[PDB]
Amino acid sequence: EVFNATRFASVYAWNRKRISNCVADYSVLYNSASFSTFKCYGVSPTKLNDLCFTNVYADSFVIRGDEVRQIAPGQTGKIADYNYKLPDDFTGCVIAWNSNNLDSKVGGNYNYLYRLFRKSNLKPFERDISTEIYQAGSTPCNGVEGFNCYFPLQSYGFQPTNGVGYQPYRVVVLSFELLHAPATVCGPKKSTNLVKNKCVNFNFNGLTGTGVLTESNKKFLPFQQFGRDIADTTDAVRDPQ
Amino acid sequence: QVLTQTPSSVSAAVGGTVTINCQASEDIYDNLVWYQQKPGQPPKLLIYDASTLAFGVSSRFRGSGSGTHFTLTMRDVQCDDAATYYCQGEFSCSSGDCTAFGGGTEVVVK
Amino acid sequence: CVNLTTRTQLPPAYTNSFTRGVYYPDKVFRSSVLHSTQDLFLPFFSNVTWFHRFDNPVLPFNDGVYFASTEKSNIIRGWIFGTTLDSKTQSLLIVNNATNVVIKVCEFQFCNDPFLGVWMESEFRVYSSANNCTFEYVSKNLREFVFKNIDGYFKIYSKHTPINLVRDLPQGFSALEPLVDLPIGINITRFQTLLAWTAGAAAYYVGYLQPRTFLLKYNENGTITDAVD
Amino acid sequence: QSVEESGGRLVTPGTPLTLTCTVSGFSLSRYAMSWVRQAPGKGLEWIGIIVDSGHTAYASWAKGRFTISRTSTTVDLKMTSLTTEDTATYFCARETGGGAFYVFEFWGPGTVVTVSS
Ligand SMILES: *[C@@H]1O[C@H](CO)[C@@H](O[C@@H]2O[C@H](CO)[C@@H](O)[C@H](O)[C@H]2NC(C)=O)[C@H](O)[C@H]1NC(C)=O
Ligand SMILES: *[C@@H]1O[C@H](CO)[C@@H](O[C@@H]2O[C@H](CO)[C@@H](O)[C@H](O)[C@H]2NC(C)=O)[C@H](O)[C@H]1NC(C)=O
Ligand SMILES: *[C@@H]1O[C@H](CO)[C@@H](O)[C@H](O)[C@H]1NC(C)=O
Ligand SMILES: *[C@@H]1O[C@H](CO)[C@@H](O)[C@H](O)[C@H]1NC(C)=O
Ligand SMILES: *[C@@H]1O[C@H](CO)[C@@H](O)[C@H](O)[C@H]1NC(C)=O
Ligand SMILES: *[C@@H]1O[C@H](CO)[C@@H](O)[C@H](O)[C@H]1NC(C)=O
Ligand SMILES: *[C@@H]1O[C@H](CO)[C@@H](O)[C@H](O)[C@H]1NC(C)=O
């Protein structure tokens, strides 16, 4: 619903979604070639399936293609400084792809707006919605459009005849963070097949050991997981599968 | 909407270098190309994206610039470089007239 | 929300704890093994408060709560937990309504007298505002519960039993099995129960836990049959 | 990839004339053909472009009196109400690859259209 939906937010009005209590799968996106650019900072996307994060933030927007370079840590641009600013120590990355077939119109798709003028460069990860008229003269414009009273918001001319730099590009930025809180977001790990009646090195749910695992005839309780003997001897029963 | 090329004409010796400036009335990012038109021959694209040398062209031609100002410099101009050069850049869309061509410059080597 | 003061003031009664409030500390299975543990428990033969009519004042959450209740109409519905309960900080919320359990953890503009109205329920005035949320969750007889918070984890142990007594904690033994875990790192100090115009009759017993040492006997099937302070 | 064109003739003002560009060695449905012109001894002028999908773009100075059409192997351009200042040389130019519009790496030999009495 975030990677490919019917409505994506604007660059200046980007949409934030919180991903938590999710079992994410980063292998499918790594293998998918439908995305134009996907390269990430701090953590290699190959090993994203291993690291577990407490919460993830996905911000979706549609920008100009030539502007996809501006969306990076320590980058200076127009939409970078006035619409979406990234922190220098940003953890995560963006996934961007050309979307001229959906986000452009024959007469020009004018539903996408971006801010050109504002008081000063905004802090990273800040949302601006106010459409106050940017005044450049000494006299107060009184919020009335006219001379020397510029409108900061302007619409992109998305047309199929434009170049690849001017084609609309759908970008979803994934940001990962951790703090003194339990982590919940990570992959499904892996479960190799089980073999019986053979001396094996087992790892059940984070408990490791060596021994032979035979079929057993004993009754547990639904919530019970491990097994024990008269002195701290593990007899694991509950298969995680 | 307006592309400007300076100077209109300039000459230099064989063992010399010259520069050409192309200015755009609007921000065009780096989407700018150059051409060389010999007398009676169709133009040949020399540099595209204002910094990438085209296939089969020499390395004595270099391009730089970004935004609204671009510069093409020729080093050790030979007698074969005597032709006309033009700059072209993409200009947004609906706002302006798609693409436009520059006025061009003439180069003659003594 | 709604301010109601038609309550007859009275100091709360006390009743003997007897031998209630033994819970399985973990998922380990043992058979015919007498095991010695040291953990937070309710001391045996203690005196616990017996609240009552309508009486639902704030009760501090020192280290853990043993909450018991017996009734026939389920007037008790849920619980509020937290520290300030003024939406200025995090505040747990659990409602075991007729439909299903609903659990939230964010800040709520709790009023001084939250309650539920009832027969068809019409009134829902426990809180007025809720912003910046973090977690959500939807899932003759005596109900016994134990609530604890350790290392930023919330543990709920529950047990339902049939009783024949009238106005006291039945004299017997019954182990408490773990039910639910919540992964939320909230520092917590206080809580308040729920009740469901017209006034009904309800009474719930509250007991406070402390660090102790216990001995537990497991039977052939691993169920706890007896315990020793 | 060879791109050629033809249609040069001497015509009176106001007489429509069509010019056909023939491609060879590539697929037209993937690449964008464009029209440019230059006056004798003057600078280059841009006429229009047709994208591979089929959408059309023109120039403001043209005022909207050109018409560029596409088919199997004939990118054709038609004119109405010729004036005496349209005497120039026309070319059809190809692109580098998918996308990357307005590059013009391959050009036609060149044809001259003259208007006089
Ligand atoms: C939206 O993106 C998802 C990416 O997971 C697409 O799901 C897969 O798409 C590929 C390519 O079309 C298929 O080969 C897979 O079979 C799809 N997976 C499943 C589970 O169906 C999804 O198709 C995309 N939506 C649309 C409308 O294309
Ligand atoms: C219910 O009663 C309480 C206390 O009588 C009210 O709380 C007071 O509210 C006023 C105005 O909101 C504050 O100025 C006081 O400081 C509050 N009391 C305290 C002790 O802080 C509450 O507003 C009443 N609610 C309704 C709905 O009448
Ligand atoms: C685990 O998933 C498999 C996959 O279909 C299923 O057959 C099995 O019943 C599941 N078992 C549990 C305990 O969820
Ligand atoms: C009964 O409860 C009261 C309440 O404070 C307490 O003081 C008293 O010691 C308790 N009696 C016994 C025998 O525990
Ligand atoms: C929202 O709550 C989180 C903790 O869950 C906190 O870090 C953040 O500062 C809060 N934001 C606001 C605006 O209250
Ligand atoms: C305990 O809770 C209080 C809020 O009542 C909080 O300010 C404090 O930080 C918590 N303790 C620790 C160690 O965080
Ligand atoms: C264990 O369960 C069996 C039947 O499930 C029952 O016959 C037996 O009495 C139980 N053990 C104990 C100690 O109650």
Image (cartoon, grey):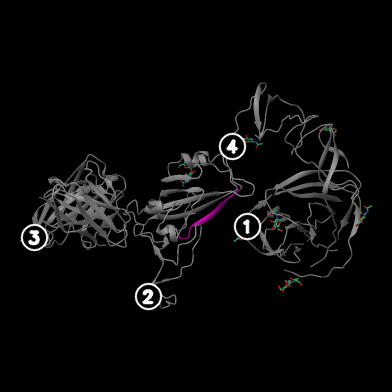
Q: Say which residue label 3 marks.
A: D12
Q: Say which residue label 2 marks.
A: A146
Q: CA distance from mark 2 to mark 3?
A: 50 Å
Q: Closer to the camera: disc 1 or disc 3? A: 1
Q: Are marks 4 and 1 in contact (CB under 8 Å)?
A: no
Question: Which quadrant is home to the N terminus of chain C?
Answer: bottom right
Q: CA distance from mark 3 to mark 4?
A: 79 Å
Q: Are marks 4 and 1 on the same chain?
A: no
Q: CA distance from mark 2 to mark 1?
A: 43 Å
Q: Say which residue label 4 marks.
A: A189
Tell me, for residue C133, which label it has, or none: 1
Q: Is mark 4 within 8 Å of ligand 3?
A: no
Where residue A91 sits in the image (x, y, percent)?
A: 52, 48
The amino acid pointed to by label 1 is: Cys
Q: Earlier in the sequence, mark 4 or mark 2?
A: 2
The amino acid pointed to by label 3 is: Thr
Question: Which quadrant is home to the C terminus of chain C?
Answer: top right
| Residue that lies at the very extreme toward the top in this rendered image | A198
Q: Residues within 10 Å of mark 1 (few under 14, many from 20)?
A: few
Which of the four quarters of the rendered structure image does ligand 2 lie in? bottom right
Element type at marker 1? loop
The amino acid pointed to by label 2 is: Gly
Q: CA distance from mark 1 to mark 3?
A: 78 Å
Front residue of C34 and A42: A42
The amino acid pointed to by label 4 is: Lys
Element type at marker 4? loop
Q: Is mark 1 within 8 Å of ligand 5?
A: no
The stretch of residues the image draws in magenta is A12-20
